[PDB]
Amino acid sequence: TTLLNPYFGEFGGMYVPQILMPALNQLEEAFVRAQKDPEFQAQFADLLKNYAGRPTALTKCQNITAGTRTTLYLKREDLLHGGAHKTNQVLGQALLAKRMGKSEIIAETGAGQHGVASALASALLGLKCRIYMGAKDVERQSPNVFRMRLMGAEVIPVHSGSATLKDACNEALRDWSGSYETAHYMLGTAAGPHPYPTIVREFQRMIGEETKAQILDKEGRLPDAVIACVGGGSNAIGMFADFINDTSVGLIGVEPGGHGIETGEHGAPLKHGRVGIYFGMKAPMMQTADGQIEESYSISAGLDFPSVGPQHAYLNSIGRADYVSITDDEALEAFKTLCRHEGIIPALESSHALAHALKMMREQPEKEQLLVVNLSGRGDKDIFTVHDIL
Amino acid sequence: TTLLNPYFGEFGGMYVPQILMPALNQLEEAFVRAQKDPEFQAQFADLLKNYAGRPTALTKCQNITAGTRTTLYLKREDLLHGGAHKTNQVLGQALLAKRMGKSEIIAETGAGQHGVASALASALLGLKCRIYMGAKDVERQSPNVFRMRLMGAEVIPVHSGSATLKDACNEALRDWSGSYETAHYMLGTAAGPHPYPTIVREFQRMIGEETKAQILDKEGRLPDAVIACVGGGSNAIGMFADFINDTSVGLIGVEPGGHGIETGEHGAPLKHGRVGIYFGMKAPMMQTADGQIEESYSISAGLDFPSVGPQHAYLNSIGRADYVSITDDEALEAFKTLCRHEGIIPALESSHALAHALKMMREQPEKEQLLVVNLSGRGDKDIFTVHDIL
Amino acid sequence: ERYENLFAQLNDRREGAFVPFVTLGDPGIEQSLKIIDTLIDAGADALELGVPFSDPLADGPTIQNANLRAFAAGVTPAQCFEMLALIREKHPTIPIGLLMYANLVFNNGIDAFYARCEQVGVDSVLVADVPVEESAPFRQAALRHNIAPIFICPPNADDDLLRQVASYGRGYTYLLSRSGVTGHHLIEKLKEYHAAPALQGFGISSPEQVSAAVRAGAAGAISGSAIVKIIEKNLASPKQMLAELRSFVSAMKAASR
Amino acid sequence: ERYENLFAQLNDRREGAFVPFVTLGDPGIEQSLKIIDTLIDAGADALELGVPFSDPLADGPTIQNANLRAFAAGVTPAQCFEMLALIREKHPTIPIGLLMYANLVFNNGIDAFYARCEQVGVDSVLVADVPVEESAPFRQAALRHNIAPIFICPPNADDDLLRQVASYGRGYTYLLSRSGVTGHHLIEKLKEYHAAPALQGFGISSPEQVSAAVRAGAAGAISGSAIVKIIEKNLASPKQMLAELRSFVSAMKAASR
Ligand SMILES: Cc1ncc(COP(=O)(O)O)c(CN[C@@H](CO)C(=O)O)c1O
Ligand SMILES: Cc1ncc(COP(=O)(O)O)c(CN[C@@H](CO)C(=O)O)c1O
Ligand SMILES: O=P(O)(O)OCCNS(=O)(=O)c1ccc2ccccc2c1
Ligand SMILES: O=P(O)(O)OCCNS(=O)(=O)c1ccc2ccccc2c1
Ligand code: NA
Ligand code: NA
């Protein structure tokens, strides 16, 4: 039995070895208690405000929408300490770990952004941080690896499997299965076994809460739609959460289309994958006809999680949220356009969300619409990639 | 005649060719008028808040001062859009250019940070931006050069002289001397001919204004001292300005000591140079016994301006502000310490200010003192440099 | 069925059961079939066979590499079931248990998976990443097809869990020797709750451990990594591999008598 | 003194003055001294000599490289003054003007600088980066040492500036041909205000420009880059350099008669 529902419709659950259930139960109880603790909320708010830099701005594009009836705002998570939305929830999870009396932190990372977030939070809060990262990713993310070590984190390459994110995810769970007594697993997205999809959403919810307050102040009404890229689902559910009960507000998630859905080289399991059971949850995923887990391809390393958060699969199933895909080329064009017309360098992940907003605008230029794109992170990290391609 | 005093004691002035005086007079008049225009102030405030991300946090270090009676706060300019304080004043100068009816922007840059700031502001406000950069710096700052071009800016290598900042400064003035009718020169620091030292200070003054409000709210009193690195003097005068009349508040500027003052390889003209006349102003500078202008050496590319703002030389002369130096090694240690104990990666420039604060703390650990260090920028840009050295 | 008979027989001889584990298809289909026959001829009372999976998040480096080697041979679930049918056609009484990961069971339908197990002659299925909390559909499908659903009793298991494991489990109760991945009081309470005979697993790699488990009250012991290690260090020597496996298994089984 | 005599003499011949500019020490001390002698022998009425400076922010690429070449030869201000003394010892009447940048004048004391100019025989000093607004100490020191402080009259100069330039200037008034760096109505008003004779500079590189300036009312014309260009394209040919410089200067001066 659990205190909270581990499922979102048919999606979710706690598919982990029996030995790990006590850890999940403990975490769920610690989370529920923390959520009712004014002292915990105050500490979390203080860190978000005075350390991370919240609230983040809501920027109105004044050039990219010229000639159309689209008004576009960008929620500036690129300005959060660390350069991405990842920082929000790691601060919350780090506080939870300390609440349970844990002194060690285990984290997985692909692009390394969550790894950096985990390392900075651990350095600030005095936690021993060890990070698992696929060997292939370590090779492609030397900068982030060095930042993690500079901040005192221990980076561990994972050579098993495909040597990428999913493999790092496995190693994290393997480690935790025998160290949960003193170590907390700081999962980086709104996926994995319950209570993680729930915890990550609640610790990223301020994105949507701020956006709502800011858009009401600036436009006097709610947006017609909020748009966010979907790798694992954390930045998107963070933006969506506070708007779920506002039926008039569209919720659009953008998965990576890679070289094109028809090529099979993409990372869009929600709309083009098949439901399976892996990484502790029942959710749509990238898998072979036999049931072997595959990797997600995208020009952006951050949209590499081969599955998707269960709440997104649920929101899609009931028609509350709509999911689409954007290709490498579409994301690249959005990246270049924002740089040149707004002076903001977006993360390639976030560029997928922007690319879809641009499409909504361009396809029907005379359609009056108020859109908000969650700019999940800055793209200084993608400068070289964009450079080599161009 | 001028509307404002071009001098700070004996320092400052307008030492430019006769042909450029009309441009300086026009700029001074446009500035004075803009400062009395509620509409201009509102536009500037809107950009600072909704585009750049002001106000920036004032972060209390909770680990680096343990065991001492020093309480240290960091003014987080590293969280400003662009990653450094440079963004504040470029937004103001870009608005001034438009107020005068100018459509083109000329800028000089060494490390490239101001170049990036100028490019992003120009992209946002629809100004044609051309940036002069010493050929040597272009070679050492490929990332920033690409960011400038991505944002639509035209980067022009300067091969004359030593092919560095001072040479780029010359080229900018050469260009402006024959294009001031349609182009505005967006000087990057609180130096150069009047009215620039004044304009840059007023357009960076919010750093100190916010710090004062924030420290009063958090500690109920003013700091014992505010500390900032000094390259040209903009981030430091931005922090100092609102505190100048608060006699109890110490103002400490930190120049780069390079390999050591005694080696001659440093960038500390205020305390170890000699007053001269160059770049349109009378100020202390790096120069040979004959009077030829030299370059400033520092591990940090940003503290490369071979002279210093006239207001700093004045504040030092009357004893209101104190200036010191910090070596490459001291800055490197401060950089590593902040990364590991606070989870913040500081710019190597800013690390010089932090290094001095650390010295004030360590030299007299039982001295009760409330210090604020201006963290002028983030150091993701210095990761490789710190890596190679280590 | 086969487990009930095995334990009844072993009990009559006052001996414990020794059950080795190997990955199907490691290092190849042919060599794996030969390895399995050697294990049986050496004294194996039952078998624990793993179907190669891309992400064995419950296994240590040893089994991880076993899965990798099998994938290098192109071993698939379909081929594993062909191997299983052949093994059963050759050995009619030895209990055969599969070590699965949930997605391979869920992939083509849970009910369909257990139906296939029943048709090739499999006796039990242990789904590594399915805790009692998510076990309903798996245990139900298992029972409908006369397959024993294997449950895990951790070392820090509370009374509540003990009762559930004892009531839902069949064939044998898996007694975890420790936390982590592959590489006395609980035993008594399991018997009190009429749980399926207990088999201790994880870390068992020596004869004395097999004797200790039996004396503790367990019906036997399972050994995997220790077995797989013999395979991984004799790849270039097929014959010696079988010879060493035989000596190992014969030594472990002797400890159970 | 020398300027007043030169213009008085030129006026009596109804001819304009041709004043070439070169960087002292470019491409070397010896060749520079020879270049200067050739200019004088070719018809130069006066000279404009630049002291190599690290940051000539008022000069275009041509002069920029002239300064660079001089620095390559290790030319310093001290050596420039030695050259100047020698030049004056050889040529007693030709007006000699220096093109300076403020720091070189301020370096060892402004008064001291003009005193040195007077002792070696220099006639005027133009400080490129000192506008009328900052000229007080420079013009005062110049006058105390009988040195003519050269002021710049831009093409878009207002009446206020015209009056200041006419009152503060001596020797000759510098008439800028355009804005930017090195590479009729104002003339009349200057005469109305008793300003020193006007010399047009910047962009003057052809004989007809020299004739146009004189007919416009100017007392003469200055040419720099055009002169320096002849030097920069004959480095490997010292003799031809002097030969080409002579032909150029003789042609320019002829246009002034
Ligand atoms: C800026 C930005 N925007 C979007 C995402 C995608 O994840 P999300 O869907 O959880 O929000 C990431 C994730 N990055 C993951 C996986 O690579 C990490 O380990 O750093 C990101 O860094
Ligand atoms: C983060 C940071 N902190 C400090 C400074 C020094 O200048 P300041 O003294 O004007 O504040 C710089 C300057 N950078 C100059 C000179 O290299 C540029 O052209 O980008 C900076 O980028
Ligand atoms: O000697 P070893 O390798 O340590 O352990 C033997 C494991 N083989 S096994 O019995 O097939 C096996 C494998 C993984 C499991 C996950 C969690 C519940 C139980 C499990 C049983
Ligand atoms: O043919 P050129 O090179 O275009 O121009 C000749 C310049 N030589 S000069 O007269 O020594 C000279 C040089 C620079 C100046 C800066 C601004 C005021 C006037 C100046 C006079
Ligand atoms: Na995904
Ligand atoms: Na300096």
Image (tube, coloured by chain):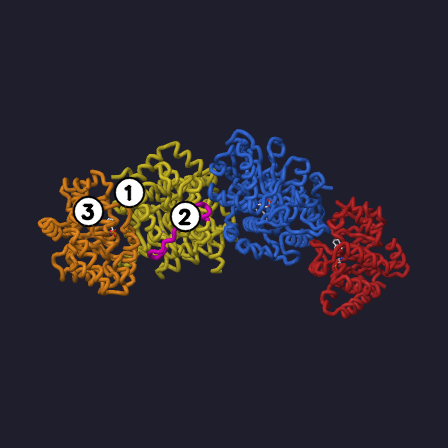
Chain colours: A blue, B yellow, C red, D orange
Q: Are marks 2 and 3 on the same chain?
A: no
- Chain under label 3? D
Placement of B305 over or under A334, stated as above or below: below
Rate crowding at label 3 as few (under 14), some (14 to 19) or many (20 or more) other CA atoms within 10 Å.
some
Which label sits in the foreground, 2 or 3?
3
Q: Of A128 and C199, which appears nearest the observer?
A: C199
Element type where label 3 sits in the image? helix
- Please, is residue C206 above or below residue B363 in the view? below
Residue B154 badge: 2
Q: Is residue B370 magenta?
A: no
Compute the Cα span from label 2 to label 3: 39 Å
As measured in the structure, the alpha-carbon distance from the residue carrying label 3 to the one carrying label 1 is 40 Å
The answer to which quarter of the image holds residue D83 is bottom left
Given residues B83 and C187, the one toward you in this image is B83
Left or right: A145 as drawn, with respect to D244: right
In the picture shown, does residue B60 fall above or below C177?
Answer: above
User: For the residue marked with disc 1, what is the amino acid?
Assistant: Pro
The residue segment tinted magenta is B147-163
**Disc 1 with disc 2 on a shared chain:** yes
Q: Position of residue B49 (x, y in %)?
A: 46, 38
Residue underneath mark 1 = B6
Q: Amino acid at mark 2?
A: Glu
Residue bearing the label numbered 3: D212
Which numbered mark, 3 or 1, is in the foreground of this view? 3
The residue depicted at 27 percent of the width and 43 percent of the height is B21
